[PDB]
Length: 296
Ligand SMILES: [Ca+2]
Ligand SMILES: [Ca+2]
Image (cartoon, rainbow, N blue to C red; front, top):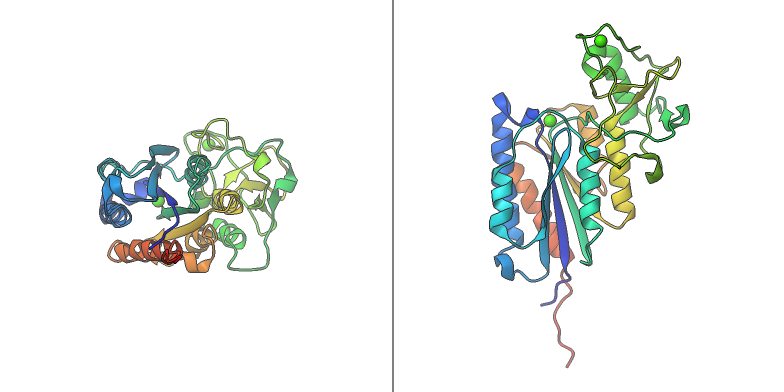
């Protein structure tokens, strides 16, 4: 029985939302993460053809392991996941692209798991108003949803810092938000811990105070979809778990679009997360089968 080599990068959001009152989220993430590792590396170091790498992220990404068959090392890093402020989903994906760049596996998969909106992203170089876009007219688009939400709850969505007298302009239906189809050349990747801020803070929308009416906002959910697209263009399959998103359309739809397609997007709760990782492992393992060697 022949299988092609496969390399998997796990990218796990460890934002503050995973802990505190919500600690069931972290605990199930840790249980299911280890379950997935064991399922994919059943022989440990002797598992032919399979390797797993691990990224966690909060306001910055963390390389927890390069590609490895070392079940114990991976499981120890998963058990050490820690809720920390910030959701730099673009950064997690960017570090996954860095790691996958060295792969010569035939099959190349990224698993992204996040329980919230992205609120951090990398700076845009030589930024102009053309790097932003307005309402699409598709009410399910992350663009239209974030604009509508920020109209309903301006200080929840838009970067603002009450400890200073500085103040953003808040959006209307005419406002423009970060695109999700910028070229890779547009992002400053010189520092994977960097984030765009206004008045010292980030957010679901980050005000670009240099630009005029109708007002312009970086949109980290769109930046994350943009980064996912670079990975898919490189040939990597993305499976995304929208984790405990509680029927919040912006969070659901923003994460759905990072996946290879809608069939690679899973809506999970802590209670049923293991079933999503089981299905992803099954899909990966079905995909690598190349039959038997029976030349004669
Ligand atoms: Ca979160
Ligand atoms: Ca302020």
